Image (cartoon, grey):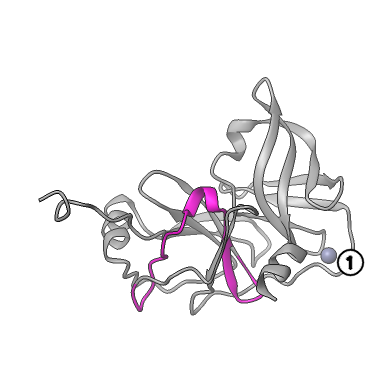
Amino acid sequence: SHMASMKKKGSVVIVGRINLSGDTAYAQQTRGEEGCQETSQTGRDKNQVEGEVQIVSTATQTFLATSINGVLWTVYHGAGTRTIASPKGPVTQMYTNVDKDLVGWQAPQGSRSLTPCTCGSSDLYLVTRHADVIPVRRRGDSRGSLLSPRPISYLKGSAGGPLLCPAGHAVGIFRAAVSTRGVAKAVDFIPVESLETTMR
Ligand SMILES: [Zn+2]
């Protein structure tokens, strides 16, 4: 029948991480293609999570997700209303705000959260899905300009990753880049204060 053939969106699946806990930033893959697809449909992810920044996938996109204050956050435009796969099965979103382009799930067992920035610094660092650390000058609440031009393609799939202050604390969640002729000049991000307001 038409109803009995209706498919369900899978879960978001954690497929790697950006390791920032050492002296070197680098990407790690923890699941390959077949395993990602299976885990998406069951919603059951056996892998132990570690770290603050996850690399996540849906069937159509790969992007990032960042743990701050006990919630793993990402962009709505990547995750939609999807559950995330976990050891206990699919986990429903704790927070969803399309107007902020923000979703959040309870942070997975084994993950750690970044500490929100208290130092007020306007010199930020964007962490990409390829573990590139890109200096960004903050221009106000939710914006920053790149210190050096990069092609907009270098930032593809980094939505949901962190903007960190010089100390490595969280200032915000990367959402979108502004470009001209394919060259990224500025970023838009969801500030940590806005996450906290969502939580309150
Ligand atoms: Zn700071």
Q: Residue 151 placed where, x, y %? A: 65, 29
Mark 1 Cα within 10 Å, few/some/many (few <14, many 20+)?
Answer: few
Residue in view at x 42 percent, y 59 percent: 82
Residue farthest to the top, as pictured: 181
Q: Is residue 14 magenta?
A: no
Residue at the spot of label 1: 119
87 displayed left or right of 155 = left
Residue furthest front as drawn: 2
Q: Please identify the quarter of the rendering in which residue 4 is found.
A: bottom left
Q: Quadrant of ligand 1?
A: bottom right
Mark 1, secondary structure of its residue: loop
Say above or below: 81 vs 139. Answer: below
Label 1 is placed on what type of residue? Cys
Q: Is residue 138 above or below residue 40?
A: above
Q: Residue at x 26, y 53 (%)?
A: 34
From the Cβ of disc 1, is ligand 1 less than 8 Å away?
Answer: yes
Magenta stretch? 67-89
The quarter of the rendered structure image containing the C terminus is: bottom right
Visible residue check, residue 190: yes
Location of residue 52 (image quadrant): bottom right
Residue 40 to residue 44: above or below: above
Residue beneath the point at 58% across and 47% down: 158
Residue 136, image quadrant: top right
